[PDB]
Image (cartoon, rainbow, N blue to C red; front, side, top):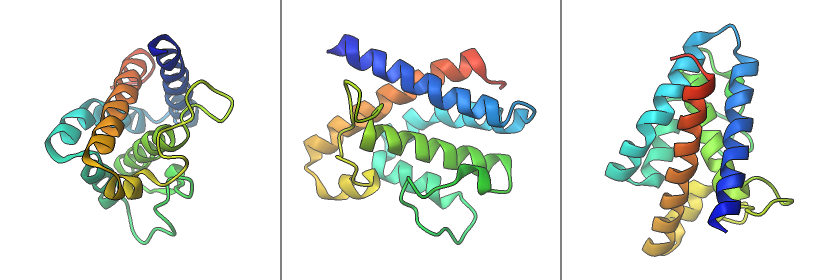
Amino acid sequence: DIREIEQERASFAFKVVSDIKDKYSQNKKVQGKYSSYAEKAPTIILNNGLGATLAFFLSKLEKPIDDVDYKSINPESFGNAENIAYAFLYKHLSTWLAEGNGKDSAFSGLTNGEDPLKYIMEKTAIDVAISTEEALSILNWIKKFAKAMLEE
């Protein structure tokens, strides 16, 4: 179960970091910023909570945004490396929490498709803490594959 969830985490991290490397093969700033933000996210989450951290990522983005629902976010539409990277990280983390690695997979999320930032404001402290553990787990995988695949 830990085995299968670790397998799904690795698969997802590979997918999302590969996409960054593919879309920004010749933009090392985007690669580097995404790597940095993935690495620093765990500390922000521990000291502020997952909800605040997701809101933090959104706070960075050029406004206005149509919809901060993670499915609606187009990371590639922002106009600097920092914004693009924060949008990606928000979108990736949110997607993991709400959908896991897909309906097909051994883990399909914790929020049942509810926007995670919203779910976090509604559920028990213990359920928020469980989602926080899961966020930290996927972030660790993302960090490892960023160090394997992306420029710093």
